[PDB]
């Protein structure tokens, strides 16, 4: 038992991290097969026109270091906000992998990197407003977020920028930003965030699986009446699809999803009254139903 | 910016995990050079006498799987509560490494494993009562906790058992339990835990580095008067050694350690009043001064 914010084992991704240097800019790249992926703002020279900027580059302007081994760029292209550098060497540590664009509410592990070297790994959620509350300093651009399914690394995030609120914005691995953000230094605001309701419910189920039951009650609620209270507390609407996803957890604990909603409603209306759930004095919303099941049942990855 | 419970990149340890099977018992082992380390209760047959139990084993009773490759045991010995299996093959992925017995208050990353396969990684502290609040299911015995310094993996923990409170107990990699625990099914109680004061202070400094300042005040306190309030709230005593360790953070933020103690005192006496610090509504104590500096300055590992 116990319940922790668990990241995926990061080794498969560590083997893909490289340093990309061009001009005075150094950041991280992702080396899969013979392509290095990195944020396009690595290129030389607000309101830049990256097409103009890139047509002016030569391959030899791109310094790619994989450890103490320089990789030479034999080609380059831009795909949305990512730059793709063709190199003459296929990464021998390339895992089996996919690129996935995730939905808000979904979680992933971030391998924070500086100068191509991994610094740490932690678990993130994509917020409803398409930011992530990460931990990123200058030099971390190009660090990636990922999930692992059996043996396959699903890359879903690459880091680009920090918003004035101290939260983070980036792209999928095909260079499309999550949310309304653009990779230029112009005024941009995240958007009002909301709490991921289905995830809070998943985490209450984790608490029950783990022996916290104090927040349960005998009441029930209608999805309709629950969502009325949710909106008042800035919670995302709970859909029937969410209820269905919460099915496996509801069945393992014997607590009807709608009964768990009654508990959450009472927790929203009354607060926690100096008590904690799973070591937290806040309602935690960065565990998906899948996260809870994986950690409470012990799924591994080969 | 941002501040997250960050684990070390786990790849160097992932390459060392193996499955050890003996009789009907399967758990994880740690393969470094030509030795596999695992908990000694993997052996056949409360109040067992493991010396008697082990003299009755043969090498061929030990099934060690490294992936889809069986390793054959050519020797075995017991060192405290760990079993050491000599195998005929040196692990080619053996990182540079050390075994370290850590002090309570120190943090480490845990690579949770089942059947030799990594499940996830998360950050833990050794509690003052020498338990860890982990996330461990049946099959996780032999998963290890570690820190990484530059290129060196410092192994500090191997998992053995769960206590009735849902917390965890284990050994260093030389098989010595942390705390008063023994690897037999007899009544054992953890001991009253306390909050790691120097770590809470480190985390308040992380909050300041990151732009939370609301909890600061103009007051100061004496170490003596602080510790009187700490004891009342079940906090560990703060020593002058702790104050010195907090020096670098105090200097970078310009807040005297003893001034930060005044803030903590006021936070203990008044609570947080519905406010949060670094996303938490509790005073967080599983970040060391070193953790804070590493994450707020971007140290990496090659
Ligand atoms: C990233 O480029 C990097 O690490 N590069 C190494 C040289 C860096 C990561 C940032 C730095 C601090 N925390 C992070 O996550 N990203 C950028 O520098 C990014 C690049 C420039 C400006 N960038 C920012 O993140 C800036 N933020 C904004 O300007 N934000 C708004 C106002 C446009 C929304 C800051 C101010 C943090 C440098 C571009 C967006 C292309
Ligand atoms: C570990 O042996 C394992 O994973 N083995 C694979 C077959 C297992 C890990 C435990 C299981 C649940 N959570 C965990 O961390 N450890 C044990 O089974 C351990 C071994 C037996 C009994 N063990 C326990 O952890 C037991 N706890 C106690 O008996 N605790 C007290 C009362 C002695 C303090 C439980 C009840 C959890 C099985 C020995 C201690 C040798």
Image (spheres, coloured by chain):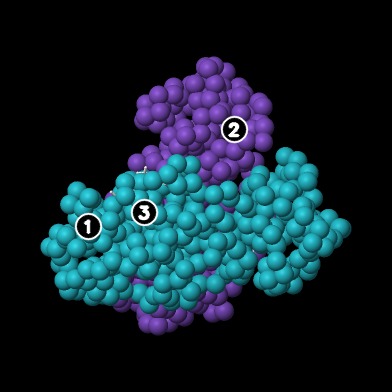
Chain colours: A cyan, B purple
Disc 3 to disc 1: CB gap under 8 Å: no
- Locate residue B80, reporting x and y percent: 46, 58
Label 3 CB, ligand 1: below 8 Å? yes
Q: Nearer the viewer, mark 1 or mark 2?
A: 1
- Locate residue A287, reporting x and y percent: 59, 60
* Residue A53 tag number: 1
Horizontal side of residue A183 vs A258, given as left or right: left
Q: Residue at x 48, y 42 (%)?
A: A165
CA distance separating discs 1 and 2: 57 Å
Secondary structure category for the residue under label 2: loop
- Locate residue B100, reporting x and y percent: 38, 50
- The answer to which of A141 and A271 lies nearer the viewer is A141
Q: Is residue A116 visible?
A: no
CA distance separating discs 3 and 1: 14 Å
- Compared with residue A96, is residue B162 higher up or lower down, i.e. above or below? above
- Compared with residue A94, is residue B178 higher up or lower down, i.e. above or below? above
Q: Earlier in the sequence, mark 3 or mark 1?
A: 1
Query: What is the crowding at mark 3: few (fewer than 14 residues within 10 Å), some, or many (at least 20)?
Result: some
Secondary structure category for the residue under label 3: loop
- Locate residue B131, reporting x and y percent: 57, 49
Could you tell me which chain the residue with mark 2 belongs to?
B
Query: What is the crowding at mark 2: few (fewer than 14 residues within 10 Å), some, or many (at least 20)?
Result: some
Question: For the view shown, which residue lies furthest in the right direction?
Answer: A218
Disc 1 to disc 2: CB gap under 8 Å: no
Q: Residue at x 35, y 71 (%)?
A: B86
What residue sits right under mark 3 in the picture? A183
Q: Residue at x 53, y 25 (%)?
A: B216
What residue sits right under mark 2 in the picture? B235
- The answer to which of A38 and B113 lies nearer the viewer is A38
């Amino acid at each position: 038992s116990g319940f922790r914010k668990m990241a995926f084992p990061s080794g498969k991704v560590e083997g893909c991290m490289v340093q990309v240097t061009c001009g005075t800019t150094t950041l991280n790249g992702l080396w899969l097969d013979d392509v290095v992926y990195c944020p396009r703002h690595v290129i030389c020279t607000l309101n830049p026109n990256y097409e103009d900027l890139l047509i002016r580059k030569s391959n030899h302007n791109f310094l790619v270091q994989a450890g103490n081994v320089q990789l030479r760029v034999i080609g380059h292209s831009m795909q949305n906000c990512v730059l793709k550098l063709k190199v003459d060497t296929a990464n021998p540590k390339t895992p089996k992998y996919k690129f996935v664009r995730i939905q808000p509410g979904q979680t992933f592990s971030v391998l924070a990197c500086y100068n191509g070297s991994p610094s740490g790994v932690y678990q993130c959620a994509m917020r409803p407003n398409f930011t992530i509350k990460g931990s990123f300093l200058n030099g971390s651009c190009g660090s990636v977020g990922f999930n692992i399914d059996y043996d396959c690394v699903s890359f879903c995030y690459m880091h680009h920028m920090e918003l004035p609120t101290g939260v983070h914005a980036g792209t999928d691995l095909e260079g499309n930003f999550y949310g309304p953000f653009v990779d230029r230094q112009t005024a941009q605001a995240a958007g009002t965030d909301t709490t991921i309701t289905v995830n809070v419910l998943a985490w209450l189920y984790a608490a029950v699986i783990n022996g916290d039951r104090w927040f349960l009650n005998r009441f029930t609620t209608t999805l309709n009446d629950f969502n009325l209270v949710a909106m008042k507390y800035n919670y995302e609407p709970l859909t029937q699809d969410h209820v269905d996803i919460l099915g496996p957890l509801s069945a393992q604990t014997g607590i009807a999803v709608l009964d768990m909603c009654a508990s959450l409603k009472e927790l929203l209306q009354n607060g926690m009254n100096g008590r904690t759930i799973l070591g937290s004095a806040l309602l935690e919303d960065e565990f998906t139903p899948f996260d809870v099941v994986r950690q409470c049942s012990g799924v591994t990855f080969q």
